Image (cartoon, grey):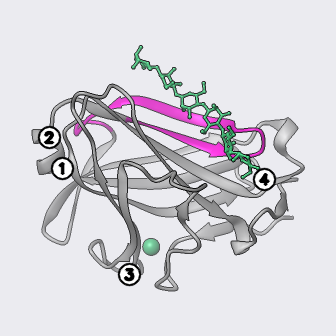
Amino acid sequence: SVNPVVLDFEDGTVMSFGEAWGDSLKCIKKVSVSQDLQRPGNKYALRLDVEFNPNNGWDQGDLGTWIGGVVEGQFDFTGYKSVEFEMFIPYDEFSKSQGGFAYKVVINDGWKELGSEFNITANAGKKVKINGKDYTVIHKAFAIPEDFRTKKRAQLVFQFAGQNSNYKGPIYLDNVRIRPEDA
Ligand SMILES: OC[C@H]1O[C@@H](O[C@H]2[C@H](O)[C@H](O)[C@H](O[C@H]3[C@H](O)[C@H](O)[C@H](O[C@H]4[C@H](O)[C@H](O)[C@H](O[C@H]5[C@H](O)[C@H](O)[C@H](O[C@H]6[C@H](O)[C@H](O)[C@@H](O)O[C@@H]6CO)O[C@@H]5CO)O[C@@H]4CO)O[C@@H]3CO)O[C@@H]2CO)[C@@H](O)[C@@H](O)[C@@H]1O
Ligand SMILES: [Ca+2]
């Protein structure tokens, strides 16, 4: 009985993704919409140009979007049960990089972590070829807890943190969905 919120970038825009608060991007140096992953029925993705410093065990940056672009809006999560996303990292360059990275998916209403993973390296997830290039692909859904299935501050945050990584390159996000489907 609820309509999924589908952040697929298919309008050719960043769909309000950018800093979550002033100067939050940090290791994320640029946020843009890209056709690098263009393929049947999926023309655009969110490109995050990142730089991690290998001497830092937690080289953090925070990317936010407001649902509907409404800054400080609230969104009724009643009936929504998961947040799903796909993440893509060029395989060859990532494999050559040292260390790894962590990510978190958060609803920023008192900072509520939905899920996270640590020590991601190139052999995480699945290796997929898109436009002549291999990618590490992470595709997950995290639960929205029952106590958040109500009106909450409508900022979704993706945190990235280099963990002694020297990776300098893109990370892509696509198909970020707030879904009634269970995680
Ligand atoms: O705009 C309105 C209002 O906003 C205010 O800004 C807010 C902002 O919107 C947001 O809500 C922010 O929330 C904070 C939050 O309160 C809390 O501090 C949170 O901390 C996170 C942090 O971001 C990281 O995710 C951190 O990760 C740790 C890992 O979980 C793990 O423990 C890790 O372990 C490492 C270890 O460090 C070491 O390398 C080794 O031992 O290996 C381990 C890994 O195996 O360490 C990580 C780093 O600590 O987790 C913590 C939670 O525990 O961060 C968010 C985001 O900043 O709050 C602000 C307010 O402060 C204001 O601007 C206000 O004026 C505005 O009106
Ligand atoms: Ca897309």
Name the main secondary structure of what is drawn in magenta. strand
Q: Are marks 1 and 2 in contact (CB under 8 Å)?
A: yes
Q: Verify whether residue 107 appears in magenta.
A: yes
* Residue nearest the observer in this picture, 137 or 107: 107
Q: Are marks 3 and 2 in contact (CB under 8 Å)?
A: no
Q: Which mark is residue 121?
A: none
Q: Quadrant of ligand 2?
A: bottom left
Residue at (23%, 27%) from the top-left corner? 55
Q: What amino acid type is highlighted by mark number 3?
A: Lys
The earlier-in-sequence mark between 3 and 1 is 3
In three-dimensional space, the C-alpha distance between marks 1 and 4, rounded to whole angstroms, equals 33 Å
- Residue behind mark 3: 43
Q: Residues within 10 Å of mark 2 (few under 14, many from 20)?
A: some
Image quadrant containing the N terminus: bottom right
Q: Residues within 10 Å of mark 3 (few under 14, many from 20)?
A: some
Quadrant in the picture for residue 35: bottom left
**Extent of the magenta region:** 102-124
Picture layout, residue 134 above or below residue 100: below
Picture layout, residue 99 above or below residue 5: above
Residue 164 in sight: yes
- Residue behind mark 2: 95
The earlier-in-sequence mark between 2 and 4 is 4
The earlier-in-sequence mark between 4 and 3 is 3
In three-dimensional space, the C-alpha distance between marks 3 and 1, rounded to whole angstroms, equals 20 Å
Residue at (20%, 50%) from the top-left corner? 168
The earlier-in-sequence mark between 3 and 2 is 3
Q: What amino acid type is highlighted by mark number 1?
A: Tyr
- Residue behind mark 1: 91
Q: Which mark is residue 80?
A: 4
